[PDB]
Image: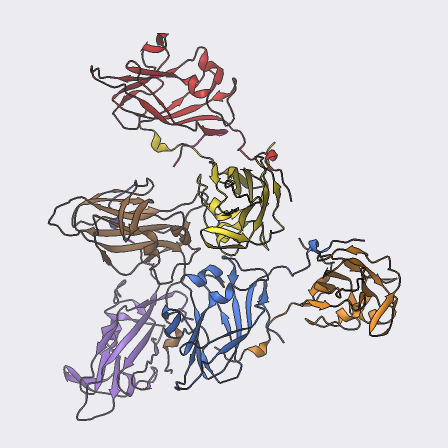
Chain colours: A purple, B brown, C yellow, D red, E blue, F orange
Amino acid sequence: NTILPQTGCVWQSLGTPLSLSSFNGLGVRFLYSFLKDFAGPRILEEDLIYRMVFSITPSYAGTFCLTDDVTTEDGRAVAHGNPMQEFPHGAFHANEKFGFELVFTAPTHAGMQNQNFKHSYAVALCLDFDAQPEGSKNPSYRFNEVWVERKAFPRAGPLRSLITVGL
Amino acid sequence: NTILPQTGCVWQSLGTPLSLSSFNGLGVRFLYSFLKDFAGPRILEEDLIYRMVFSITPSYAGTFCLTDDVTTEDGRAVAHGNPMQEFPHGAFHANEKFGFELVFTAPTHAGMQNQNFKHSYAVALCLDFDAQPEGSKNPSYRFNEVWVERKAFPRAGPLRSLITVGL
Amino acid sequence: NTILPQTGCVWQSLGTPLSLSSFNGLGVRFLYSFLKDFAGPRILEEDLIYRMVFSITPSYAGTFCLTDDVTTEDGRAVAHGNPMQEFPHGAFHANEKFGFELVFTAPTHAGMQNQNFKHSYAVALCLDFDAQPEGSKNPSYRFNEVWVERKAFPRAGPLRSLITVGL
Amino acid sequence: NTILPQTGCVWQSLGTPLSLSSFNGLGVRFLYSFLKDFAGPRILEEDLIYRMVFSITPSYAGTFCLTDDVTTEDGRAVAHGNPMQEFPHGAFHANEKFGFELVFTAPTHAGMQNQNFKHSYAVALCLDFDAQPEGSKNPSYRFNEVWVERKAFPRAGPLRSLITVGL
Amino acid sequence: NTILPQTGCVWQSLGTPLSLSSFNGLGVRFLYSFLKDFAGPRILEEDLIYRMVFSITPSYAGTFCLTDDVTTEDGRAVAHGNPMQEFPHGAFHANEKFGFELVFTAPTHAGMQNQNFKHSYAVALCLDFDAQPEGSKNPSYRFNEVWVERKAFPRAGPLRSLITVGL
Amino acid sequence: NTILPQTGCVWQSLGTPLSLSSFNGLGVRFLYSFLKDFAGPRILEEDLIYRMVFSITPSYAGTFCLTDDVTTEDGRAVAHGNPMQEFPHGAFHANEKFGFELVFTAPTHAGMQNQNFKHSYAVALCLDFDAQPEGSKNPSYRFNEVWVERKAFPRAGPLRSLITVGL
C-alpha cells in the first residue's frame, strides 16, 4: 500500500501545503529551500539524504524537469539549461495531479549530505508553461505532499515538563 | 527528556487545539469524546488503551477532578459527584498551565478496551469555577496537548498511487 | 453441599432481592437487565459468562420458559414465541419455590461474551399466569437468589486509604 | 490499592453499619461483641485471629484508646484505665473519618485464639468526648467498616437444593 | 473451479435473492445490513470477517463504488463522497451481470471484527444511474449471490429431538 | 445436540418440504423417489448410502411401516405386505410429529449402493389411515425434513466466473 524504506531508514513529511506563482512564464525552486523547512527534528549539515517524493497540482499545461544550470540576475529566474537524465521529466495537463520520486547517489556511496545541495550539487525544479496570450493570468501551482528519506530517529513523545499536578 | 512508553507501546498525539466555554459555572467532557477524534490510524472497539496525558490553560481559578457520576437533563451538565481517588485532582490559577497523566487498569490485566469507556467505565473530566459576580464573563479553557498510549503500529509513509510519471 | 465451579472460574451473587408485577397476564425480563446490576466488580463487554442460577417465589400457578422472540409495542410485553429447547421449562404452583440453572455455549467454544446478550442472543425469561377472573389481583413474583459464573478475580479487601492514625 | 493478607490468610467484612450513643460522656465496646457477629462462616473458639481494621465517624471531638481495665457496676461504663502502648491512640475532630489497624500476638506465635478475647485478653475500645455544656446532646458515633483477617476458607457458592426443575 | 479459502476458513452463503429500487437516482446499502442476515449460525460481535463476494443484475447503465462518506437527512440517501481506492469500482451496462470481491484488513492483522462495520469502519455500496428523462422508471437492481469468509465451524446435521419412534 | 456421523461421512439435507394425499386410504412412496432429488452434488449409481432420517406431520391417525412387497396395477397403490423387522414401525396421532432413522447394510459390508434401491432392494414407505366415514376428506401428510449420510465431499464455495470487474 505504501512505499517501503530501506534497511535502516524512515520517512518524514513536510507538514503543510504551499502555493506559488508563475512569475514570467516559469517557476524555479531549489531543493535546499524545501530541505530547510522540515522541523520534526531538523536536518543537520552532515545528514545523509536518500530519496524525495513530490505531488503538485498546476493550473495550466506544460513540462517539468530537474536542471543544475539556472540563469538569473535579479529576483525572477529567466532561463534554465537542459534537463538532467538521471531525474524524471515529462508533461502535465491543467488541474491534474502528477508526482515523482528522486534518487540521490555519490561516486562511492548511496546518499548525499545535506550541505552539498548548496555547493556543487545545487539542483533546481523548473516548471515551464506554454501559452502566451495577451489577456492572461499567471498560472499558479500548489504542492500537496513532500517526503524525505533519512536515517532512523526515535518517535515523538510528550515532555515530562507537561506534568505539574500529581497523584 | 520525554516520557518513555512501555515494552511494546507507542505514543500518539491528537493534532489540534480546542477551546470550550464555562456554560453555567462548570465544564464537563467525557473521555470518549476525545478518543473518537484520533485519526492517524483510528482506534477500534477492542483496542487496549494504557495512559493519557493532558495540558489545559484556563482563564480563571478553580478545581478539577475525574468523576463517574454526572447529573444532566438537557444539554448543560448541572452537577457531578465526588472525585475518584485513583485519578489526580487539585486546584489551578488563572492563565497558568497545568497537566496530569491518567493510568487505566482492569481487575485482571493492564489497560482498558476502547468500547468500555462508553458502558460501565464512563469517566468524565469536570472543571469547577468559583466566583459568582453579577457582571461577569464565562471562563473559557483551551486544550494544548492530548496524548494516548496504544499498541505499536507501523510508521506512516507515502502512497504508491502518488507516483504517476516515471524514469 | 454446593455446586462446584469449573477449573478456573468463581461464583458471584447479585446481593439483593427484587419484586415485580404480573402486568397483563405475563411477565418478561431480559437477561441483560440482570447482568448490568452485578457490582462487586462490574462485568465488561468482552467478559465470558458460563452459567446462571435462579430462585423465584410466585403467588399463583402457571408455566415458565426461555424464549428469544418477544412481541411488544409499548411498555407491556404482550406475547412471546415458542420455548427454546436447550433451556429448561415447566410449571409451578402458588407460594412454592422453584429454581433452575442455565448453560451458555458458542459454536466453537464454551461461554458467551456479555455484549452478545444484547445483539443476536437476546434471550428473555417469561412467566405465564393462567386464571382470568374478573375480580382478581395481579400475580406478583419475587427473586430470591441470582448467581453467575465468571473468570476468577481476586477476593475483596480493605483499602489503604481507610487508615489515618498510626502507631 | 488494597492491604494484602499474609501467606495463608483472607479478609472478611462485617457487612452492616451500626450506630451507638455517648451514654454519660464516653462509649466502651469490647472486641468480643464485634467478633460474635461475623456470619459468612462463623468463628469458632479455637480459630486464630490476626488483624482488625476499623472506620468510625463521630459527631464531636475527643480521643480514643485501647484499654484492658474498664470500671463499671451497672450498665454504663463509667471509667477506664490507661491506654495500652502496642495499640494506636490519638484524637479526632467532629464529622471526620478516622481509622486504624490492630495487630495481635502471643508470647510464642502470631495470632490470638478467639476464646481468649473473653478470658485474660479482654481488650475494649473507648471513646472520650470532652465538652460538658448544660444544654447539650449525647455525641453519637457510627461504624462504617469492620474487617478481620483469618485462615483461608473456600468461597461461597449456590446450594444444590436450589434446583428443582431440570432439563 | 471455485475460489479456495485460506488455511483455517470456510465460505457461507446468504441464501436468498433480494430486489431494491433506485429511489432518487442512486441506491445505497451499508455492509452491516447484509451481515445481520446470515443465519446458518449467526455472526457475533467479535467474529473476524475476511472477504466478501457479490453478484448484481441492474436494469440500466451507470457506475458503482465503495465509499465511507454518505450524506443523508431523512430516508433517502442523497449524495456520497469519493470512491475508496482499496476497493474496486467501474461501470456496468443494462441487464448484464457484474461481480467483485472485497478484502478487509487492519493495521496489525488480517480481517475486521463484525462490530467495527458499525463504528469507524462503516463502508457503504453505492450505485449511480445516469439518465434523467422526464418520462422514466426507477432503475431497479437485484442481488443474486452474497458470500462471506469466516472462521471454520462444524457442518450442519439433524437434531436428536427429531427421532420419536424407535426400533 | 446433533447426531454425529461416522468416521469418514457427512450429512446432507433435501432442502424443501413436500405434501401428498391419501389417495384411497393409504400412501406409498419408494425410497428411490427421494434419492433422485438431492442436488447439492447429485448421487451417482455406485455411491454408498449409510442412513436416512425422516420427519412427517399427518392429518389423521394410523400406522406406518417399511415393506418390500407393494401390489399395484394402475396409478394408485392398493395393498402392501407385512412390515420388515429391521426397520421401525408404529402408530401416530393426528397433527403430531413423528420421526425415525433407517440403517442399511449388506451381507459383507456396511451401506448399500444407490443403484440397488431399484433392483432387488426396492423398499417403500407406507402410511395406513384407519377411519372410513362416508362424508370424509383425504388425510394428507407433509414431509418436514429428509437427511442422508454419504461419503465426505468438499464444502460449497463461489465460482471464479462470478468476478468480472477487478482491482
Q: Is residue C94 above or below residue A30?
A: above
Q: Is residue D4 magenta?
A: yes
Give the left or right position of residue E78, taking residue C109 as reference. Answer: left
**How many callouts does the rendering have?**
0
Q: Nearer the viewer, residue B83 or F115?
A: F115
| Left or right: E100 as drawn, with respect to B110 | right
Does the rendering let one see residue C47?
no
- Which residue, as the protein is rendered here, is positioned at the far left? B135
The picture places residue E163, in percent across and down from the top left corner, at 73, 55
Q: Is residue F117 left or right of residue D11?
A: right
Q: Position of residue C59 (x, y in %)?
A: 54, 37
Q: Where is C107 relative to F45, above or below?
A: above
| Secondary structure, magenta segment, majority class | loop
User: Quick check: A124 above or below B157?
Assistant: below
Asked if residue F34 shows in the view, the reply is: yes
Query: Is residue A56 on the magenta stretch?
Result: no
Query: Residue E104: where, in percent of width, then height?
Result: 48, 67
Farthest residue in the top direction? D73
Between F25 and E160, the one lying in front of the other is: F25
Q: Quadrant of residue D67?
A: top left
Q: In the rendered image of this protein, does residue D75 appear above or below residue F123?
A: above
Residue A139: x and y, percent? 22, 85
**Magenta part of the protein: which range?**
D3-8
Please tell me which residue lies in front, F137 or F72: F137
